[PDB]
Amino acid sequence: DTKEQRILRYVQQNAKPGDPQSVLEAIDTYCTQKEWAMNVGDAKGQIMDAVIREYSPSLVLELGAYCGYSAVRMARLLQPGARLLTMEMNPDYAAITQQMLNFAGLQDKVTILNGASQDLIPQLKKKYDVDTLDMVFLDHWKDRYLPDTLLLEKCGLLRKGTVLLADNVIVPGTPDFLAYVRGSSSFECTHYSSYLEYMKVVDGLEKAIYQG
Image (cartoon, rainbow, N blue to C red; front, side, top):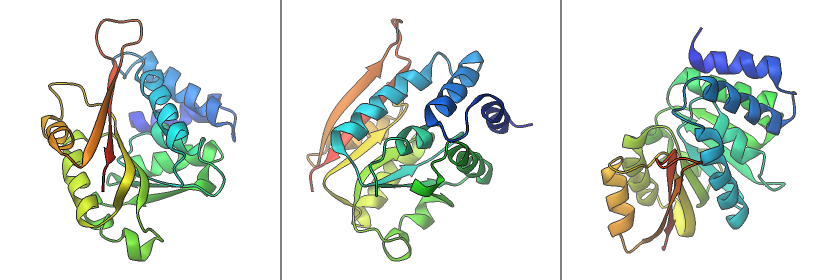
């Protein structure tokens, strides 16, 4: 029906329920069969994995979601007691992301919030138990990365050592987000460009560690 829901029935037919590696492989194979320019799955996932593993976050906020690849990717790795909160505005993306997490057997570790980042971020402290975040994954919507970052700061959600990891920041792309976290003395930045075997970047990611 819709391509995001096609990723769904495909996972439903090929993956083993309760096996997130199988679900990720299924999502990857499907999107690579067609949509991703090259193999963005492998290109982003292994960076995502190293970052989660380096910092051991207990509370991760994902900002943006499309077909749930990134949420499955993180959630599979969360230590016992750790949680993922994911916000996504498009109700169908939120629904597919939820269904994908259920399939993979990770629904107990995640909360999907279907709403605008701008309404939901201010609600995070009172309505969910949040003090500060350990990690923020910024995902599908490049023009939201800066304003969401600014609003997390405003709202006192970042502490010294909070990791922001932003997907799909390839130059000339996201000029404003990059210019902000780079020129800011409150963020230490590391840029990852995944080529796979190619000469052109398949995915680029930005890690920005908030300094307090």
